[PDB]
Picture (cartoon, rainbow, N blue to C red):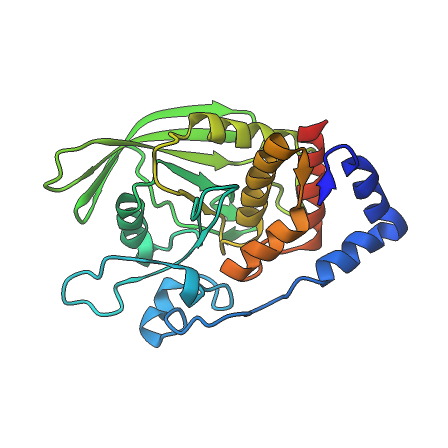
Length: 278
């Protein structure tokens, strides 16, 4: 643990010798499958996984209500992750695929999620990273109707507000998608400033009474892990004057494969929390 006051010295020493401290620390994490994922690797679930190597662990996967007469329809490539002092405060997932747009929305509904965090652009370096799973006006995904109700554009992100409805349920829920568009085509942001501003918008706007925050990038590990770690750590820093980033990542990794996918992402988390604390 690092007192937020020794944070700069800590980060600085870790950067010495081209970041030997960080390089070695990051290498201490376990890369790859560290737990069973029998359901994720089922052939019948193969088309629900974006990246075959970034799939959902059994012990923490988010289960779906089996769609009547459909075995295996209880799977979504997503995992629960604890918040500062809130169990299962987040769901780390992959960017929906056309085949999984419905599974995504029904999960959002069933989990009573109010905020969707998207930290990837639709196409990067020529590659499609996530399908457009939301409508520009309105769209009915089987029994879930989604209506775009507002769009707010800011420097490095856009906030899309939706009026979401389920058939036969006399209710209209406001669900906001916080789309961070400021993450570079390569590497990590040059200034953590924008993502920090994005985090506070999510924290401030998110109803303390709703279900877990659904976070996703493309695979649902790197930038998803960055947002989540930064979010939890600001909570700890606030309530304790201490940050424990290493153990936070280690813990997220027990929940889902390779959270915080690169060492550069790992160092960025430190820069962001340091800036926030300064």
